Amino acid sequence: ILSHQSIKNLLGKVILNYSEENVRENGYDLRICGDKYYELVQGAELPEKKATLREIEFKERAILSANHTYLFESCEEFNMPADLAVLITLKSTLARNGFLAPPTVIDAGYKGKVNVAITAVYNSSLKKGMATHHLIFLKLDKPTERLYNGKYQGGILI
Amino acid sequence: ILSHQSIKNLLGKVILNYSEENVRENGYDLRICGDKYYELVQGAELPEKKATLREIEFKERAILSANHTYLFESCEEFNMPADLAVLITLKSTLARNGFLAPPTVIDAGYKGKVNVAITAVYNSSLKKGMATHHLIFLKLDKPTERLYNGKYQGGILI
Amino acid sequence: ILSHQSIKNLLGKVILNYSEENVRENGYDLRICGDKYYELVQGAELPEKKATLREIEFKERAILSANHTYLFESCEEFNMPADLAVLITLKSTLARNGFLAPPTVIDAGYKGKVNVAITAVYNSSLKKGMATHHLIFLKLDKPTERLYNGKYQGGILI
Ligand SMILES: O=c1ccn([C@H]2C[C@H](O)[C@@H](COP(=O)(O)OP(=O)(O)O)O2)c(=O)[nH]1
Ligand SMILES: O=c1ccn([C@H]2C[C@H](O)[C@@H](COP(=O)(O)OP(=O)(O)O)O2)c(=O)[nH]1
Ligand SMILES: O=c1ccn([C@H]2C[C@H](O)[C@@H](COP(=O)(O)OP(=O)(O)O)O2)c(=O)[nH]1
Ligand SMILES: [Mg+2]
Ligand SMILES: [Mg+2]
Ligand SMILES: [Mg+2]
Image 1 (cartoon, rainbow over the protein chains, first blue to last red):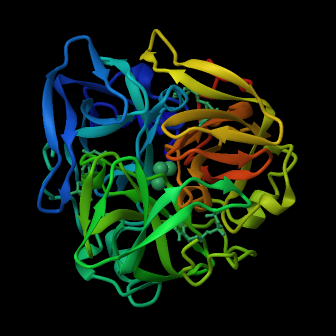
Image 2 (cartoon, chains in turn orange, yellow, brown; image 1 turned 180 degrees about the vertical axis):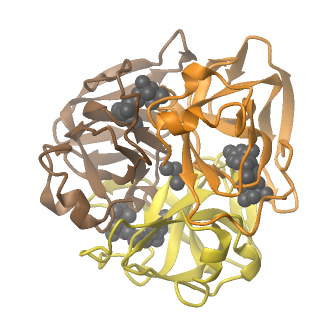
Image 3 (cartoon, rainbow over the protein chains, first blue to last red; image 1 turned 180 degrees about the horizontal axis):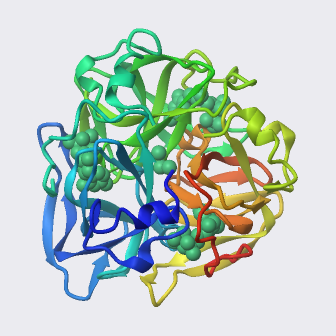
C-alpha cells in the first residue's frame, strides 16, 4: 500500500481533477461530482440486460430513496500505470451513516473517471462534491502484461 | 498484489476449473456455477442458529428477489499455498447493476470451491456460469504457520 | 499482508483487549462488544446531518431488524503504527448468513476501538462478544508522513 507521501506524488499524473487535502494517511478520498447521477429503477438480467436507470440532474445534493442503488461519477479522473491498481473502499463516515457499497477495483491501465454504486439503506442525501470513498493504492508485483481495455474505458457509465 | 502474468502461472495449480480469459489485468474473475444455488429465507441468530436456506435447481439462470441474499458455489476450485491469500471483491458490472456483496477473504491453506453471498437490491437475475467476482491475490509477508483447517474446508456451503 | 505469526507479534502492542485464538491464517477476527449498540432509525443528509441513532443496551444478544444498519463497538482497541493500515472485511460466516458490511479501513496512527456498521438483510441477531469481521493488515511502502488525527480519534462513535 502507498503512504500519504507516495500518493501525493501521484497527483496531477495518476489522479487528475484532484484535491490536495484529500490525500490522507494511506489513501485518497474520492469525491462524487458530475452533471447527473443515476437511480436504478428496474433490476438487471445479467449479462444480457442491464439495470434500468433514471437520469437525475446533479445540482447541489443527491436525494436517495431507501432500498435503491445510485450511480455517481467521480470528480477525479484516473490514468493508471501498468504497475498500480486501486481498491475502492467506502469512507467509514458513509458506512456508519447508513450507506452501502461493495468493494470494487480500478485496474492498471484504466483511464478516465470512475462510476461508483452507492446503495441507500434509508431515505437520505449526499452533497455534490463530498468525499464518499477511500482509495487504497496497491502496487503490482510486476508491470502487468495486460492493461485494461474493457467496455468501461474512458469512464463509461454502464 | 499479483499481476496478470503471475496469476496465469497459478492456473492448474492454485486455481482449478479455470478459464484463461478470466485472468485479467491484476485479478481473476470468479464464476458462479453448481447444480444448485440458495436463497436465504429466514434470518440467522448467530452463532448458534444459521440462516434458513431454500435450495434451488441452478438450471440456466438464477432468479433473485429484491432484499434477499443468495449463496452461489464458484466454478473454480482453490488450493491456496501457505504464502497467498485472496480478497474477494465484486465485479463493478454487478455493482453498477444493483447487486451487493461484502468483502471476504480466501485464506492460505484453504482447499475447495468457495460459496459467495450476493444480495439483490432489485428483482433480477444472473446467468449460470457468468463472472461475478474479482479476485485480488495477496502475498503474505512470510509463509503462515497456521494454514486454514476450519469448518468450511473442502467447500462446505454453510 | 501480514501472516499469522506477524499478527501474533502485534498482540498487546497494536491490538489491545485481544484474544489469541482470534489470530487466524492471515488476519484477525474482530469481536463486537461494548455496553451499547446502535440502530440507525433515520436517514442522514451528509455531510451536515448525521443519521439518527437509537441507543440500545447490549446485554447478551443484539436483535436486528431487516433493512436496518447497526453500529457496534469493537472489543479490541487499536494503536496503529505509522507503517500499518488495516482493511476491514466481513467474516464469510456473517456474509453467507445474511449480513452486509462495506469495506472500510483503519488508518496508520489511529488509536482506540473501532465502530463497525452491519446491515441486516433479515430480522436476525448477533451474540455479544462474537467475531464478526476479518482484519487484513497492510504494510505501507514507507512510514506515513500523515498520521491519523481525524474526528474519530479515540474511538468516537459517529
Ligand atoms: O466501482 C468501480 C470500479 C471500477 N471502475 C472502473 C475501473 C476498472 O478498471 C474498470 C473495470 O471494468 P471491467 O473490468 O471491464 O468490468 P468489471 O469491473 O465488472 O470486471 O471499471 C469503475 O468505474 N467503478
Ligand atoms: O465469500 C467467501 C470467502 C471465503 N470462503 C472460504 C475461504 C476461506 O478461507 C474460508 C474461511 O472460512 P472461516 O475462516 O472458517 O469462517 P469466516 O470466513 O467467517 O472467518 O471460507 C468462502 O467460501 N466464501
Ligand atoms: O468501519 C470503521 C473503519 C474505520 N474506523 C476508524 C479507523 C480509521 O482510521 C478512522 C477513519 O475515520 P475518518 O478518516 O476520519 O472518516 P472516514 O473513514 O469516513 O474517511 O475511523 C472505524 O471506527 N470503523
Ligand atoms: Mg475486497
Ligand atoms: Mg470490500
Ligand atoms: Mg473490503
